[PDB]
Amino acid sequence: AMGYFSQIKDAMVFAFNLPAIVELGTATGFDFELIDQGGLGHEKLTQARN
Amino acid sequence: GAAWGGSYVNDFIDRGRVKKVYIMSEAKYRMLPEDIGKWYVRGSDGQMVP
């Protein structure tokens, strides 16, 4: 399916299998939050993320 | 009440944080019993009455 769905130009379509436990992520994955600690704003936080 | 005790009208955003908006008399106009006469209400006629 991902072989077929990679050639769909209009959208960005993915197919995946059910995780064993949804809350558990990939053992190699990390969940990282980029917090705006100084009232910088949305644009400055986006620039920092970029 | 608004002049002599202050009133909380609504919220505003200050550096991205929701904060309150207050209206109150200036200090020099709410200090003495004689300052009560300085305040005028508007009647139906459109004229200010102390």
Image: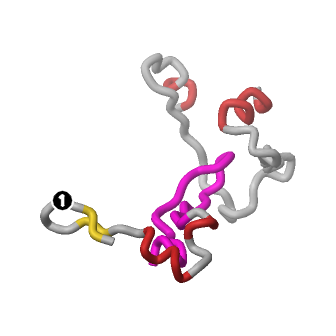
**Which quadrant of the figure contains the C terminus of chain B?**
bottom left
- Residue B33 belongs to magenta span: no
The quadrant holding residue A41 is: top right
Classify B35 as above or below A19: below
Q: Chain of mark 1?
A: B
- Name the residue tied to disc 1: B46
Between A47 and A3, the residue placed more toward the observer is A47
Q: Residue furthest left?
A: B45
- Across and down, in percent, residue A46 comes to 70, 31
Applied colour scheme:
secondary structure
Residue B43 in the figure: left or right of residue A44: left
Q: Residue furthest bottom?
A: B33
- Across and down, in percent, residue A1 comes to 52, 32
Classify B31 as above or below B40: below
- Across and down, in percent, residue A13 comes to 50, 32
Q: Residues within 10 Å of mark 1 (few under 14, many from 20)?
A: few
- Residue B18 belongs to magenta span: yes
SS under mark 1: loop
Q: Residue furthest front?
A: B34
Between A36 and A11, the residue placed more toward the observer is A36
The residue located at (60%, 55%) in the rendering is A18
Between B23 and A11, the residue placed more toward the observer is B23
Majority SS type along the magenta span: strand
Amino acid identity at mark 1: Gly
The residue located at (79%, 44%) in the rendering is A34
- The magenta region covers B1-25
